[PDB]
Image (spheres, helix red, strand yellow):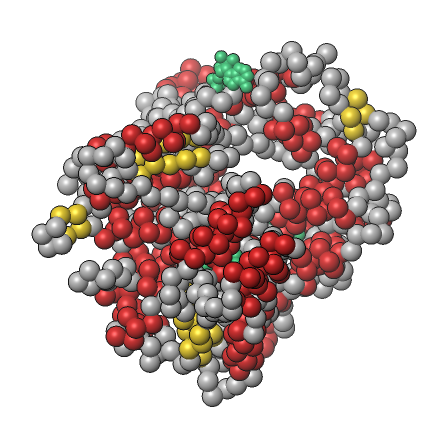
Amino acid sequence: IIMDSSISKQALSEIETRHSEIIKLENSIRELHD
Amino acid sequence: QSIINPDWNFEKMGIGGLDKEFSDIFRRAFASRVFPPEIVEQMGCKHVKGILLYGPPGCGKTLLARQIGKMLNAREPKVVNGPEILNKYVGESEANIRKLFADAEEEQRRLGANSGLHIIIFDEIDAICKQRGSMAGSTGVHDTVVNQLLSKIDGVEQLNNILVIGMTNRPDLIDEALLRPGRLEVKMEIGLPDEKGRLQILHIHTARMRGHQLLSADVDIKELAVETKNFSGAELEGLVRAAQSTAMNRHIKASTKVEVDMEKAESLQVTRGDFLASLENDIKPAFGTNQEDYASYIMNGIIKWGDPVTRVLDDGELLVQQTKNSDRTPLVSVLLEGPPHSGKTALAAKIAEESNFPFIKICSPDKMIGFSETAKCQAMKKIFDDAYKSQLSCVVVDDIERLLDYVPIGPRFSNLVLQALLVLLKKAPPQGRKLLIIGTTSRKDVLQEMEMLNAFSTTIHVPNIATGEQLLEALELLGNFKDKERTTIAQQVKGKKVWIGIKKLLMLIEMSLQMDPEYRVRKFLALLREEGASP
Amino acid sequence: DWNFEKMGIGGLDKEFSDIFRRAFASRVFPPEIVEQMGCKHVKGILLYGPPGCGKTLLARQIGKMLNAREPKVVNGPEILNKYVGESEANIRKLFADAEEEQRRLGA
Amino acid sequence: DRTPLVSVLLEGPPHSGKTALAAKIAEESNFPFIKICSPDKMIGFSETAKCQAMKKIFDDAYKSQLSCVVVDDIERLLDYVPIGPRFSNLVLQALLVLLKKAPPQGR
Ligand SMILES: Nc1ncnc2c1ncn2[C@@H]1O[C@H](COP(=O)(O)OP(=O)(O)OP(=O)(O)O)[C@@H](O)[C@H]1O
Ligand SMILES: Nc1ncnc2c1ncn2[C@@H]1O[C@H](COP(=O)(O)OP(=O)(O)OP(=O)(O)O)[C@@H](O)[C@H]1O
Ligand SMILES: Nc1ncnc2c1ncn2[C@@H]1O[C@H](COP(=O)(O)OP(=O)(O)O)[C@@H](O)[C@H]1O
Ligand SMILES: [Mg+2]
Ligand SMILES: [Mg+2]
Ligand SMILES: [Mg+2]
Ligand SMILES: [Mg+2]
């Protein structure tokens, strides 16, 4: 009636440019370079 | 041209005694895909897009992978190792798995009902596709991968230019969904080579040495092929390499500093003795045989101490000849009876050996020390089950009374074993097969009581020495006492009664041969007279 | 330079001679005959027995015998990591230089 | 070599000095491997445990060149009591099969 269990975790490929810096790319492309 | 190339080959490639399997798979698959499309449309049927290969280790699956990779005129095969698609970052495993099928889907879109076929070989497929039951582990990468692959192979969209060949070493650890019809069908088993594939393999792996004249005329390939039985290709290659290694080292000398005998090893040939030594002490088959049993049950050979010994062997030969050439009686049984210490097991083993039945086994209690009755029943059932897979067989069950755990206080024994043995003596094998059962026991009356003696078909006695002349003849044929000693021994035994078994005679001679020469005969006579007992 | 006396493993003679025969024999003979015979080399050895008859001394001394790169040691279960699909990478990271040299030089 | 297995039995009245004459015979032989299987090391064991212990002790003797084994106080290994009578059957069967099992070749 007992079974101890182990776990395995995974990391996340955190991306600086997947949101809020695509808007910053636009602010760098459409605004700064314009 | 559709797919195949003019040079079928199949002998230079390296693949050996796999002809029926390849022909059958070429029949089932690669047939509808090679034919005028109009006829196929006239019947209106689709192709098969899944093959699974499995077998015991070392049969040639991986070699088939590469050879198929070469034995086609398609675009190119994509071979991916099993447990290499799992990745740490979230979502990358599914990206890797879906990245494989892009080309096939794109081409089918461009040319529907046309184009070639793309073949993907999933080596070690059992690594990633496990049962989706629990897995008792956080995250569902293992479940997600199998679900994604299952959706891709079969789904709302229809793909007809892809074939997957999944090779596994043990089918037990495979998800149920894939083996169901519509996902992976036409599953084949690759077994061991029987007789001709073995010779073909040994020729393929030895062609080179004979090409350069490196094999001495003494060696015979057919002799080695016949001698080696229950071998797998890997075992044959290992044996060849072991013989090569025995010679290579034979031509070298190194005790203090490694030194080669150049100009002494310039000429090098491999002799039959090297092969025999390698086969005897280097390579041993994994399936296993019964050499130890056969050499251990008949320990001191079989001698001829009188008329009775020949009659039993003659009757056994008659029974064997009967089981060979009859169709009304597919099952025959025989019982060997006699007083203790008379050599019944050895005679049964000799009778079994005399016949050349392909399958022979001896089920003795020595292997079941400390087993409860359930385990005994399971083991006996497994032995008989395996014996039920050949055109001829012979199973020897010796020392019956020790199987039932019989003790004369009460008395007491086991019932499950008795019932199982009473039922297995009357079940006929599947149609068109034969079987011969031999039993060994020492207490006939007890068996007669339990109503088992009427299940057997016949009984043969096994008597022991019962006359002075027979004892003298046996002593002469053993060759221990000679000249005056035999004279006095014959004088003492005045043609009187001698109720002694052969094994006890051996033991008495050995015990008597331990003192000084003057007293040996006296001790032997004293022991024979004291233990001599009466009938 | 190498002598069986210097390694001080007295007691085992048949075992060492057999191991030298079966494995380190195809890499001593001249290099042309072996080619003709068309034989690959054996890759693998397994040692087992009671606790302390000299199994780690044999490994160490065989490692120090050869005139090649130094051995790569894996102390027990030292290839297990938490992140999914990292033990496989760890094991796969061992047969790395061998593949490179095999693909570069050849024989 | 005709008889690679020999067994003997010492019998007599109780309190007579039998367990101290098997030990001397075993000692004076100077055999390489000697082991004594007495029932005071198996207090409270069930039948299966006794069978396993005896089997292990006998297996330890098949991996030597020649050896002697002592089974003292048989009447107590397979429990016995005059009332009834009662006893264990598994132990008796194990002993009766182990007393006629020749060892591997040449030992
Ligand atoms: N029919 C055969 N023809 C030629 N060689 C064979 C044959 N069967 C076996 N062999 C030899 O034995 C080996 C067969 O095993 P192979 O290399 O194919 O791996 P495998 O059997 O797939 O291994 P695993 O069982 O672990 O998946 C090869 O080295 C090959 O040379
Ligand atoms: N003609 C012979 N027939 C049988 N055995 C012989 C003969 N000549 C010599 N022997 C020796 O006698 C032995 C016969 O005794 P064996 O070891 O087979 O026991 P057994 O008769 O089955 O014993 P038990 O019935 O007490 O279990 C043979 O193994 C062989 O060593
Ligand atoms: N054959 C041998 N010759 C010399 N020393 C030995 C031998 N076998 C073991 N030893 C000694 O045992 C120790 C190392 O044993 P070890 O390699 O740890 O055995 P294991 O790894 O099997 O436990 C050292 O002190 C070594 O000298
Ligand atoms: Mg493989
Ligand atoms: Mg018998
Ligand atoms: Mg160690
Ligand atoms: Mg006592």
Residue at the extreme left = D83
The picture places residue A33, in percent across and down from the top left corner, at 46, 16
- Residue at 80% across, 32% down: B251
The picture places residue C66, in percent across and down from the top left corner, at 67, 18
Viewed as shown, does residue B268 lie left or right of D102?
A: right
Please count the marks in the image. Answer: 0
Question: Is residue B326 or residue A26 the one in the foreground?
Answer: B326
Relative to B532, say whether C9 is above or below: above
The picture places residue D77, in percent across and down from the top left corner, at 23, 42
Question: Is residue C83 or residue D20 the one in the foreground?
Answer: D20
The picture places residue B130, in percent across and down from the top left corner, at 37, 47
Viewed as shown, does residue B162 lie left or right of B208?
A: left
Task: Choose top left, top right, bottom left or bottom right for residue B21.
Answer: bottom right
Question: Is residue B150 or residue D70 the one in the foreground?
Answer: D70
Q: Is residue B160 visible?
A: no
Question: Is residue B141 or residue C14 the one in the foreground?
Answer: C14
Q: Is residue A25 visible?
A: yes
- Residue at 23% across, 62% down: B408
